[PDB]
Amino acid sequence: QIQLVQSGPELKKPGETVKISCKASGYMFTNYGMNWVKQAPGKALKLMGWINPYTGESTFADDFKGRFAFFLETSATTAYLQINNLKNEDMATYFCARGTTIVRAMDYWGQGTSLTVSSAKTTPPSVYPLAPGSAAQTNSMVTLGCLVKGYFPEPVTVTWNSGSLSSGVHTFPAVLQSDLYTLSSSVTVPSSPRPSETVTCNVAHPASSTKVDKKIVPR
Amino acid sequence: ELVMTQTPLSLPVSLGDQASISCRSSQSLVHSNGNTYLHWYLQKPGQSPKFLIYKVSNRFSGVPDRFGGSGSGTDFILKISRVEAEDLGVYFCFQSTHFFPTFGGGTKLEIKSADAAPTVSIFPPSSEQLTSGGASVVCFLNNFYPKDINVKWKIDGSERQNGVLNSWTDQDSKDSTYSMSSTLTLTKDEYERHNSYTCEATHKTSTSPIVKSFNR
Ligand SMILES: CN1C(=O)[C@@H]2[C@H](C1=O)[C@]1(Cl)C(Cl)=C(Cl)[C@@]2(Cl)C1(Cl)Cl
Image (cartoon, rainbow over all chains, first blue to last red; front, side, top):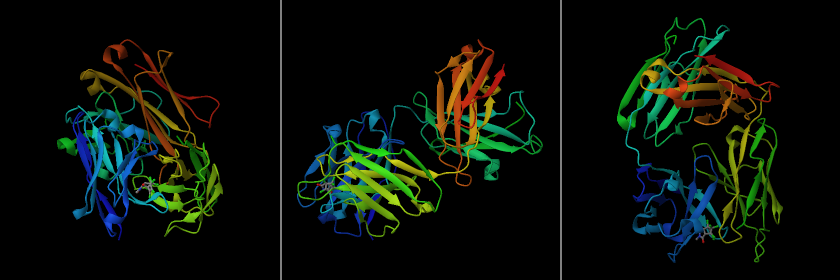
């Protein structure tokens, strides 16, 4: 019954302000405090603070002063986390979580809200074929790849042979290089079916409505 | 502030086996009121953290019998008698005895399997990237185990620790191995200034690094 449904992903530029909602249900919204937690990519959970119930007081960790606010629209049992004057270090995922006073802990957590802060403008990726460079060679299998470079924002969807190829593939998380993202994906197939049987990566970027195919030819 | 230190960072286990992880506070968590506010949470890849144990040894509703929390003062332990696949993920301890509640850094419960050397492949800058004025050399070190691996890049026989971006996949669903991608990005001028480009992988499966190179 208890549900904490958070608002969708956010894309903002430094200096802007963001409002992340947390819609609660299945419980008496006015009897529990709402906590907010920040988690930077692959890092530990960090408690930002919370907003007491019947009283309406908010506590903030030292790291979250001046630009942060907690408030709620009880008539709709929703809690908000407002971040003004966005900084790059504000980029992370945010969690809303119910607090249970007697135990001094958060019990039910929201699904999480990802926040990206960047001055970069939408940009479709550049897709390059990664075929072997005339060295090494024989054995039972061959690895091929595709470099998806210079796109924004995330994400990108990579498939091989329209998704028919699945077991031999490894698509890696994107990394930021100067306001822009780059990811790579490898596929390993038996050396007998290639180039005999075509192998092509398909890169799609919704953000910019982009769909690109790149057949891997002996480069 | 209360520092919560968890160990290990990664705990490889075989499903069905027992698992035990530690959480230590820089200050005793025993409150003046007698309670010890040390809790545990399970965060699954992509999912919201889940409430597991409260006040040291009390199981939150719905939490399986196999989860047991113990310890006192500054030292705590969370034990899983028989690990199931649903238990894999990152465990976090959290204290709220001392103003400004703090979390431990986490312990990732992963799968143990036999050692596996990485499969390393190097790819020179594509022709269309070059034409466009760019030059990235990519190296794949795939399906290896354990997860600890270091990759070095040498340009004309000398190490380059710059222009390098690395990315790592999560443990593989069907074979429990790990994979890494490392790409050396350099200016086209630079690329056209050197001949040899090598990708060196160091893994416990070998006394000698695995080297993949090409000379343009
Ligand atoms: C009301 N309220 C609070 O005072 C805080 C939060 C909350 O929901 C949590 Cl989740 C609970 Cl409950 C208590 Cl009490 C603390 Cl101090 C912690 Cl433990 Cl951070």
